[PDB]
Amino acid sequence: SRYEKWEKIKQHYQHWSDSLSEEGRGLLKKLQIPIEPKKDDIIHSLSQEEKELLKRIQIDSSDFLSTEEKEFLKKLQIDIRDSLSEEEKELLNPLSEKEKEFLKKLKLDIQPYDINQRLQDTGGLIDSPSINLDVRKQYKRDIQNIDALLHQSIGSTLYNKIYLYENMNINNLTATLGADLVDSTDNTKINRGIFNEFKKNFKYSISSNYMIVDINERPALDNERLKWRIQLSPDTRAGYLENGKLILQRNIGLEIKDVQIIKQSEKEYIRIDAKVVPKSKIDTKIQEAQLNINQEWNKALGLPKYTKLITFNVHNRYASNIVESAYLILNEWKNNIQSDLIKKVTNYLVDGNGRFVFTDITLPNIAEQYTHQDEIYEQVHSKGLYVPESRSILLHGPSKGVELRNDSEGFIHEFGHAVDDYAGYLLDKNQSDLVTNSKKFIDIFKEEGSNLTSYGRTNEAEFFAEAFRLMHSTDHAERLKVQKNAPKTFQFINDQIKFIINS
Ligand SMILES: Cc1cc(S(=O)(=O)N[C@H](C)C(=O)NO)ccc1F
Ligand SMILES: [Zn+2]
């Protein structure tokens, strides 16, 4: 019975609920309902020129903000444009230098106080210098206090009598597969192929924030196609939340027991059955996996066995896929790029203590970035990233890059940046730079810069990287388009590759 179960669990935590302080309650409420930034105050704090700038700016054109930072700026833009005319509003590409630098500093002032979000973004590494220091300390105090509140386990009586539930948006786990998981012809069906890709490498899950689950399964909203059914362990700590819900302790492990396609009210959903395990159990599987993929690829690249090249920075709910997808990504990388170029460049990265960082936490919270990027407004979150100061490639699992078909296409783009780096280094080892800053390629970019992908138009660095990406696509047509639409760039990259190999 739904209601008896609800009552039985509520009574279990009843003394706990009654014992909560006024501070404890407010803290628990703050967690469920994050404190949003005050739009009025933000807009008021802008200058007249900055308002006009924010008013006309194409927000989606950015490539360093999060989906949530973009969503807020969109709302901020609306309030700005309100006072305008009806005809003018109807009227209202990469960003200009002026625009980009403005958004970069503006993102510092649009951060909501969201404890769960901070935990997921950092994967628990809450000391990461990706937010204001004072806010960071407020988060630490709140999280520690919440950990203290959640001291009562579910019990050895209830843990195997109850299932708890969670509806989830597919884009939470993976934006890439989420775009094509629902059948395009029939919205009520799941694409059997994509469902297989999703199901195959999903064996375990990690929660670095506090899961808020339903005691009783509620019908999914239209964006929710994932129906988690969770069984807790006896010593899993939790707390009762009003309207039949439970707040779970952070840092729990979840073994994926079964993933099925089910029908609820004449529509297909994905059932994910999970069992709570000690997180350390999962972390061991991850660490063992990292030890393995490094051994396989050190040999394959002729690197010493003790070389730490590939890093798994995994802390979130689609954990196992981040690990398993890494194999598939590097396989494609090996297939579509000549071995000598790969070895030469990888050795350069290893000589700089560089890493291949595969992660499900946001890239500003990766040490390989933030150690060389003190300024938050310069910190970038994106699908992928190359950091020359650390000689590191960063690849963010859950997200989706612009006009990419897969993660492997993203990684090759980033390897392109490393090629851009090494080649510029070989030209002048004393004063190392990027070949894309050479007068030659700058002229090539001034001419052919718009002939490839839209994103390639950003700058000479990204252009080189996009060209390099398409030159090594599995699609032969794409490789030819570069040769035909940007022949100078085509030869320029080929020259660098030869020069690198012959070095
Ligand atoms: C087209 C493309 C875009 C991106 S991105 O994440 O959206 N852009 C970021 C800033 C990037 O280029 N990092 O190297 C990453 C890889 C790609 F191939
Ligand atoms: Zn790039």
Image (tube, helix red, strand yellow):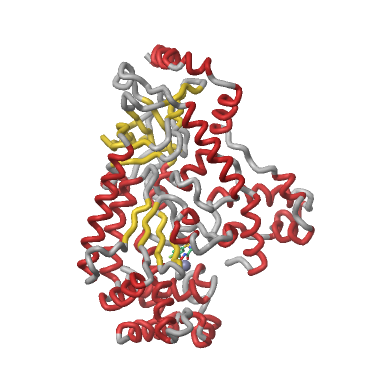
Quadrant of image for the N terminus:
top left
* Residue 181 pos. (x, y %): 37, 46
**Residue at 31% of width from left, 35% of height from top?**
278
Q: Which quadrant holds residue 253? A: top left
Question: Looking at this view, is 119 or 133 the one in front?
Answer: 133
Residue 91 at least partly seen: no
Q: Is residue 352 left or right of residue 114?
A: left
**Residue at 52% of width from left, 21% of height from top?**
242
Q: Which quadrant holds residue 210? A: top left
Question: Looking at this view, is 134 or 276 the one in front?
Answer: 134
User: Is residue 29 depicted above or below 113 in this figure?
Assistant: above
User: Is residue 369 depicted above or below 424 in this figure?
Assistant: above
Quadrant of image for the C terminus:
bottom left
* Residue 85 pos. (x, y %): 78, 53
* Residue 422 pos. (x, y %): 40, 78
Residue 238 at least partly seen: yes
Q: Which quadrant holds residue 290? A: bottom left
**Residue at 22% of width from left, 64% of height from top?**
305
* Residue 479 pos. (x, y %): 36, 75
Question: Looking at this view, is 180 or 382 the one in front?
Answer: 382
Mark count:
0
Q: Is residue 377 left or right of residue 203?
A: right
Q: Is residue 406 left or right of residue 72?
A: left
